[PDB]
Amino acid sequence: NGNGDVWERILALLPCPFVALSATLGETQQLCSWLNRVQGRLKEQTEEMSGKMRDFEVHLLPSEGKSIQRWNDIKKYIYLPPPGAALTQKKIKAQYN
Amino acid sequence: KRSRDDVYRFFFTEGVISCKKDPLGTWTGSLGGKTFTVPSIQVMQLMRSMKSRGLIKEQFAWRHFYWFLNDEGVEYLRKYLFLPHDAVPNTHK
Amino acid sequence: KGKKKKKKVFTKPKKPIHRHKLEKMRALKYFKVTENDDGSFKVERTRDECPNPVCGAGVFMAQHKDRKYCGKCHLTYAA
Amino acid sequence: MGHLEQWRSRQKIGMGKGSRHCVICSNQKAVIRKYELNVCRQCFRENAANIGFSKLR
Amino acid sequence: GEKCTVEPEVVDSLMEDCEKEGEDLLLRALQRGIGMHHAGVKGKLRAHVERLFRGRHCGVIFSTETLALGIHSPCRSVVLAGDHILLNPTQFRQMMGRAGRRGLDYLGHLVFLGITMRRIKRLMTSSMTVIKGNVQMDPISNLRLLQLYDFNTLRHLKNEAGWKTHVLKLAERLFVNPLFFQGRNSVAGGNMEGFTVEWLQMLLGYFQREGLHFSDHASSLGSILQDAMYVFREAHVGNEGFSFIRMLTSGVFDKAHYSPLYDKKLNSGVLD
Amino acid sequence: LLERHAADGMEKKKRMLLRQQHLQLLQQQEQENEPNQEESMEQKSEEQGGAQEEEQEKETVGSVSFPGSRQFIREHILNVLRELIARDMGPTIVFSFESEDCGDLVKYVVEQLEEAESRYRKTNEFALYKARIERAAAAQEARR
Amino acid sequence: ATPENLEDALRIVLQKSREVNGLIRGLSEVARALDRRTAHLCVLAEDCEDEEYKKLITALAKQGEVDLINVEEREKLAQWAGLTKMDSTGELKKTFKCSCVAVRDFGERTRALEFLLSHLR
Amino acid sequence: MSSRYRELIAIFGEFLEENDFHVRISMDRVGEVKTLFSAKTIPVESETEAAIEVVTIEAARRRDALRRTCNAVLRTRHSDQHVDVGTIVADEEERLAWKFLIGALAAKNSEILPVVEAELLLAAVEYHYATARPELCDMFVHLSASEMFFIDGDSLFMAALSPQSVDWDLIQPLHVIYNAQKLLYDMHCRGARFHVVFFDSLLWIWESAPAKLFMRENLRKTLMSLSENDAKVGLSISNFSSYYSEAFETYVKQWEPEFILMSDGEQLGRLNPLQAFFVRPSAANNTHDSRRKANYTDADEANPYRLRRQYRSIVEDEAVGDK
RNA sequence: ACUCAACACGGGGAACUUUACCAGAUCCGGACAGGGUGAGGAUUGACAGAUUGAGUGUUCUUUCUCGAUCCCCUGAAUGGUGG
């Protein structure tokens, strides 16, 4: 939906231990592999001294799995009027229905 | 509404024009000695526009209007009637 | 005195504004010219002028289906 | 001819207490005067003499 | 409705602010517990709207995507009108993350008005949002990188090698794989990449010698300008042709030569 | 099953409705277009086509049902909204994408509401309403 | 002579008529002048296309015993009548292309020249 | 600017009695003519459309479209003597030409009908094609390129035989179909498609070409995917017939909802063999569910088209379509 | 206007006008041109028929007749017995 290029520059470079924020994704591995790779390259360039601890990237997961959203139960339906109708029923009434 | 030219020729050799404030037509010198006749509203429109362009100096008293026309006025006129002048007041004195 | 703000009963066809109805190259539609005979050009007209002092110059009349007309002195010679 | 003949007509006939209008302003309410054919009571006479009038009594 | 928390004086002051900034008669519409928000509303006043509608004053508010997109909002009953102008799976997935208020109610709902019973399917059904993300390799990036390396190279000694350590770690951390998707199937792989040292040479060689990379009157500038195509005259020989670090390394330790000054300065400062 | 029966139901309804308006239109127009041919010349009291038509089709926003966009919509959007209120599911946010859209919607609704305010200036109940308040005010003033 | 004498003298006498009202500018305006034979010194620009236009002019001008002169562009003719609106930047709003001037007045040195040219009857 | 006037006067005065300048001048019957124009959904009237106009980005369009349609009409009915010949228009003319039409029909008492009818129909479909509406998208893989998507293979072939826009590289002796293989390996590879290709063939309204070009490829991909699997052959293909022609493709289109990828045009016109029978489906499409249309294209990421707007149902005619 | 300093008071005895108020139609009295308009331009007025309370060109049909300021679009100006 960008402009997904500028992002990548800032995920390659320099002490950012990073937290990043997403909803659901259908792809885990291909992405994460690239990430964790160039994380290990950050460690590599800092070596030989290593860091206070060395890069690694974790990738929150374990067992909930999109029952995060669940409890607000979004209920999807349609309007769909009968063939007739009046727009003139007008203003404050008991019941509109 | 092409009594314009006549009105402008009444201006030059006077420097002054006067008219009542009325919606019903009457001659705006009451005599010019050239015996022109114009409405009232038509006159009023002419001087109104030229006023906004800075060429006129306006005076109102009672139910009437007294129109004087500047140094600036003389310029505009001479170009429109394509004629030089020695000057309006020197001819009159 | 006192006052309010609202005017709209409305919701009809309102009037269009009158706007000029153009004829293009009006002179050439009146004056007619010919094949050249004797090296002299013969000029005729489909428009004939009205006989009144006001119209006495060049000022032509008109042509409708059921009437003839003069827009200058607002007259009718009826057909 | 058309609209122009039907606009501003019935008091260029001149009738009633319309088409008066004071000399001093142009207001036609509060009586133009017909008394000795002066006009002043619509710019009020308290405001303006310079006609030679004064209250002596 | 009856339930409001907000005191009158609060409201009336905001309402006052509407009068002066009036535009679409946001004035009238807000006074009707009836509010709009999008980009065409000024930042100030649109914020003011949402302060009412988190306080419970207003009663629907009509917005465009941007609201639930980037901002927390209390909603229950959310409504959608047409698929116009462009509605996408991603956007349906956005709105569907919204509706219902935490611990107040356990419902919330959507209503599709309602031009199709077909297109609702083709949003709902098909799941997947994935990162198919874009490559960072670009000509302009590599000009920037050039002038970065050559920045402290201009007069300095110790500073050079210190900076050179830095630029090293930068340009090694960048162009590592990137090995995304579309790229693997472009005859690289499987699934490896790197490679890109050779690209950067081809680029570089073009870019110093051409005549009209300077400018009206022709190159030279500096006096050198060959040594670009010297590194092509090293690598492309055997292709070079297999390393991951050492040949990348070599590339960035070569690295001016003489590239064209006044023009590339004016590239980098149009983009900034 | 049922959901689409009503959908396609009201769609097909609309289309055949349209055709019917083209029948009324066709015969209206037929008279407007002045064919002079039918040489009866007022020796028959039924002319300009036969029978049978002579119906009146409901107009609401130019028709009732209505496909697509920006006509259907707004007419009902007030009522969509209002039923979430009358079900007592409280507040809600409506989405339409920019620019002209959201403004047409909002505007139209302000219109409708201002409309219904005017109808209640037909003034019976509202009349007594004013009649009261005024009385109370006067009384208070007199007391003070 | 020179064509300097031709066009510039024309432009001069032209100007003298514009500043007063001897001139007639237009189509049916010019035409109706020649029909009752009130015109004196007529002039024409031919660079037009609309056939005839031209034929009407020349026809009634000789038949009315009216002097006629011919010059080239209907461009330059326009700007010598000084029709054109040029604005704040001295650049176009409308710019006229105009044909068929009549004049009902006469010059002095430009008239003197026009005798010496002897252009038309 | 009376020249133009006398020319249009000429050809009128030849075609019929001299002068339609005289009566009819108004009309009486104006609703007849004006009904006939806009029941075919071409732009005649606006002073209120939905409501009063913006007064010109709109009315300008409406005008130019109108009077140019009227030109097309006039350039038909002037036949029944000799071949079609052009017409010139600015303002006032429009009315001139308008009168010419009136007197034709009014006199001849419905000798007109099939010509102005056929013309105005054809012309209408051409307008409704190009009124129409360009976009630049992007995106291709999002909306589009999941679910059931089709491209009918005539269009496929003409995409492969397309390149000028680079005259085609690789000197081979007219085995070219590498194109097809390539495209399969583009949008299966990094797209979803669930893809279907029809070969609709024959469409045409032929010949001039060796015409080995279709049947070879038809039978080719049929054999590929039908083999059962082979890890290159899943797209998959069906047969049919009877060309295009509708009252058939309904049973398919319904069950399976779908969006669509298709080609008119470049160049190579010709008239009836290409532009005709490709254009007329686009119109068809919009009367329906609505299925929307793409392409060629001018590609990787993406292409044209059109889209989400209102339609006129029914309005039809195909009658070339040789089988 | 409401105790004395409201209530044959507002020079207020109004048929139209006056006149604010109600139903309906008309006219620019929108200056100033920065932005658009070829010889036709942009433009003004109208007989007849129709619309209409109106033998009111308001508007349309029809054609004729005319300054190019009149005309078209934003800004601004203006007038008001509106507060």
Image (cartoon, coloured by chain):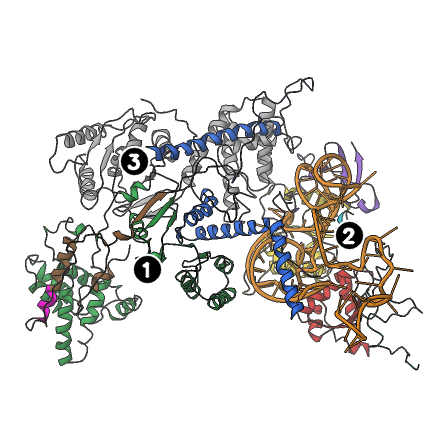
Picture quadrant of residue H249 = top left
Which colour is chain G painted? yellow
Q: Which residue is mark 2?
A: D7
> Looking at the rendering, in which quadrant would you find the C terminus of chain H?
top left
**Residue B14 picture location, percent across and down:** 79, 72
Q: Chain of mark 3?
A: H
Say above or below: F74 vs A32. Answer: above
Of G70 and B7, which appears nearest the observer? B7
Q: Which chain is orange?
A: I
For the residues labelled 1 and 2, the Cα–Cα distance comes to 64 Å
Q: Can see residue D31?
A: no
Q: Which chain is green?
A: E
Q: Which chain is blue?
A: F
Which colour is chain D painted? cyan
For the residues labelled 3 and 2, the Cα–Cα distance comes to 70 Å
Question: Are discs 1 and 2 both within one chain?
Answer: no
Can you tell which mark lies on residue E70? 1
Q: Which chain is red?
A: B
Of G116 and F83, which appears nearest the observer? F83
Mark nearest the camera among 3 and 2 is 3
Which colour is chain C painted? purple
| Residue pictured at 11% horizontal, 69% vertical | E253
Of H127 and F15, which appears nearest the observer? F15
